[PDB]
Image (cartoon, rainbow, N blue to C red; front, side, top):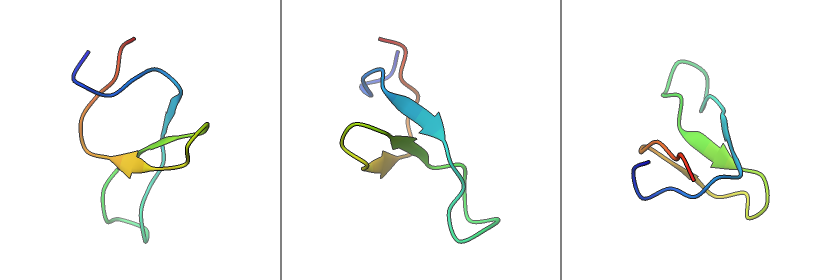
Length: 36
């Protein structure tokens, strides 16, 4: 994929903000897309 590892969700920010992805191991979030 695009720099992100597997381990992720497509959470939403404050509400409408963005679908910042969120990892569930490390619980960081981001704009790219993982695929392995």
